Image (cartoon, rainbow over all chains, first blue to last red):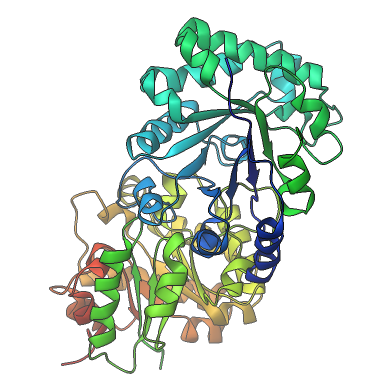
Length: 249
Length: 249
């Protein structure tokens, strides 16, 4: 019934040696809620720097990886490389990769199965666009995106998956999501897991909210019973990321 | 005369250990001092290679995006490369154009942005087996080049190297002869002369990016419009040194 609260910070395409030095120093100086599992995701070229400098109780994630150990994929990073560098997490299926870079549901599932088999943990991102929501496809889209992973991975493999619901419909659009709207989808995802994977996976899988999370709204969102944490965007670059980690204390 | 140019594209290959061994071999090699040599590790190893490698070999990234920063999960910006002391980037590699669907305009945007950020660019072009059999080799390469020429200034070409990839002879079972390669390279240089300027045509290195190894590098290098190589799998092997030295007796 209980699930450890989970806060990921996705830096996206942001950072310099100097900016990351200050950012990491702020995190190292911070007082963090011991009950919260924290993961940050630097750009791939800063992973060694971050991994060395960052407090060990915050683990590092890559922002993406590919579906093979190695080969002729110019520009791609392998899960094995991540393991080689001591990077335990990867974000897969982020809306920007799905919708700007055309990563299909099955490619996401391929990556996910491959990363898990390599011993990584996965933040698996799902969610529907404004157009899909207007079409009434919220439940169809999240079902389809999850089903691609569920077809590919074992019940035990879910142990190392965290699901991030991204309300893409409320990201850079004129719409805003309420905690109640977020809660509604998280409950739908958990029911899908119960009915398609197992009751145990539904009860133990963290489902984190990946909409616009900042210091001002995190406390309200965390009160919802099916929101198990956050995948933070722009606020992960700011000192208030600490406040978001501490949203419950 | 144009300085001979040898790039080694590791693609999605490498570990800390395997890379250590590769770099030590290069650091101990006797290299033709007239050759400009560039190595392109996977992104998560750029700091490693940049620290360890002899300073007369420059490092390249295998890809980058078109802006300095923002919400592009999984992408690296040219500004990050500059920040890390990475002077080169490979753009428009056939694997990114085909597997990852990168359009001509996207490649051209990336190229413009990288140049503006102070990088040098290895710009890859080339035609597929079907295009070549249909007789569109020059239509395709002219189109791929025109997209860049429409976006960058005449002076911007100064820090461009064109890699001709005979995609028709990469993973097709076909091999290209030096005469076939020379014929395309000569057509590319003439394209530059007639569409850009006389200077750009005579200054721009056009390097051959088909299947280059120790056994064929010497005869390719004798061709008067082949200014070097973009090496794939052999760049992972000791014979990369022989390819660098293709102009020596």
